[PDB]
Image 1 (cartoon, rainbow, N blue to C red):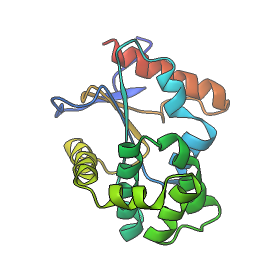
Image 2: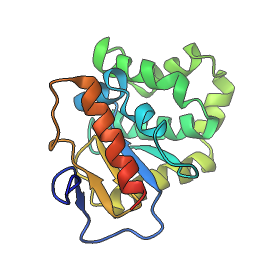
Image 3: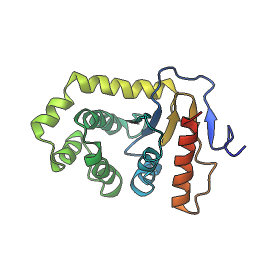
Image 4: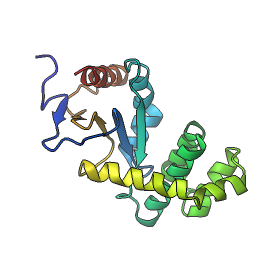
Length: 188
C-alpha cells in the first residue's frame, strides 16, 4: 500500500487507552525539535490538515537537559495553563539553542516576562497545583508510550510517526508528507 505499517509509521504493540488524538513530544534542548518547530513548522502544518474535531496536544519531556530540562517541562505547563504557547515557543527554543542565554529557571522566567506575562501571574502559575497536574499529565503521557526520544508524534495512542521513512531533499515536501500521514492515521 502507499502507507505501510513499519514505513511512514509504526504500530504500538501496547496501545494506550484514552490517549490524546494527536500527541506531539519535544524538548527545548532537542536539536531536531528546533528544526521541526522553527524551520519545518511541523505542528502547524499538521494542524492545518487535521480533520474536523481532532485536537492537537504538545508536551515537553524531562529526559534531556537535566535539571533545566525539568524546569522547562514545568515552564511548558505554565505556558499551557496561561495559553501563551505561541508567545514563548520561539524565544525558549532560541534561548536554549541559539543564544544559549537560558541557564536557569530565572532565565526561563525572563522569557515569559519579555513576552508580556506579568511576574506575579507567571509566579502564581509556576507554583500552582493546576500546573503541577499539567506537569503530571506530560509525564504520564510520555510514560504511557515508553518515550525515549524526541521529536515524536502519536495518533490515538496507537500509531507512532516514522519520519525516517521519508525524503528530506525538499523541506516543504517532507512536511506535507508528514502532515498527510498524520491525517491518514487520524482517519484510520
